[PDB]
Amino acid sequence: MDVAGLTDCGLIRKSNQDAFYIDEKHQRFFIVADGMGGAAGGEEASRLAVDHIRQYLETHLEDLQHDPVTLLRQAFLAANHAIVEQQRQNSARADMGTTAVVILLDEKGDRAWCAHVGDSRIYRWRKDQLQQITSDHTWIAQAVQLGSLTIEQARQHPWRHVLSQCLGREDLSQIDIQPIDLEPGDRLLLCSDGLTEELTDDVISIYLSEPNVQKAAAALVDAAKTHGGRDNVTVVVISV
Ligand SMILES: [Ca+2]
Ligand SMILES: [Ca+2]
Ligand SMILES: [Ca+2]
Ligand SMILES: [Ca+2]
């Protein structure tokens, strides 16, 4: 199983508030976070999220891998509290927040638990078929899903940019957690919306077809900038 990860400012943003982590030693879990907030930032929130989810998983994986939904929920809440605590304390960064998408693999490696809060995404790629696993926690996504406003078509409405869920909120209840089964040759992609605001699903699928995940990850980031690079962009590419 090969894995590559990459982050980039883009061509507009002066700093990168994205963060990611790959479990290089054991390849059990993978994390991408997209921060927001100034003063700064932002980068604080997404760093906290990645660090706390990582440390919670590291500590409790042995004990709780039989119950991944409980494990992932507690990891996310650990992250959420760490951010809220740094908020409640610090006035300037009181509104800092971040997305997170996490993949946790079962020990066997045939099953992946996908957990997320926000509009960062997880995709699975299998035999030239690209499938978005996570559903965006945005107002307009959840609108289209209902509907109406089921024109897609969705953005550009003003938001688009506005999240219905993010880490760093005392009012956090919804954490989406779902299992997906894996097959040899599948690719997994974790990405911030810096990727998917620039690249259509069709384009992403092309780049995920490259067996070399190092080249694939670099291609994705490079393509996102060619198309505009209006935001921070982060990708983690996993070959199953
Ligand atoms: Ca951001
Ligand atoms: Ca967005
Ligand atoms: Ca973003
Ligand atoms: Ca563009």
Image: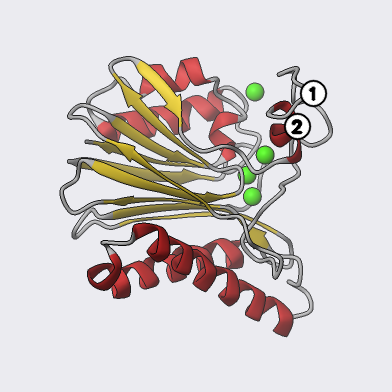
The image position of residue 13, as x and y in percent, is 66, 45
What amino acid is at disc 1?
Ser
The figure's colour scheme reads secondary structure
Q: Quadrant of residue 210?
A: top left
Depth check, front residue: 109 or 146: 146
Depth check, front residue: 108 or 66: 66
> In the rendered image, which residue does mark 2 sit on?
143
Q: Compared to 5, does 46 lie above or below?
A: below
The image position of residue 189, as x and y in percent, is 39, 36
Q: Does any atom of ligand 2 lie closer than 8 Å to the CB of label 1?
A: no
Q: Quadrant of residue 158?
A: top right
Q: Quadrant of the C terminus?
A: top left
**Please, what secondary structure does the residue beneath circle 2 have?**
helix
The image position of residue 128, as x and y in percent, is 33, 14
- The Cα–Cα distance between marks 1 and 2, rounded to whole angstroms, is 6 Å
Mark identifier at residue 191: none
| Farthest-out residue, bottom | 89
> In the rendered image, which residue does mark 1 sit on?
148
Which residue is located at x 67 percent, y 52 percent?
A: 165
Say left or right for 200 vs 143.
left
Pointers 1 and 2 in contact (CB under 8 A)?
yes
**Please, what secondary structure does the residue beneath circle 1 have?**
loop
What amino acid is at disc 2?
Ala
Which residue is located at x 37 percent, y 17 percent?
A: 129
Which residue is located at x 76 percent, y 66 percent?
A: 95
Q: Quadrant of the N terminus?
A: top left
Which residue is located at x 45 percent, y 23 percent?
A: 204
The number of discs equals 2
Depth check, front residue: 34 or 177: 177
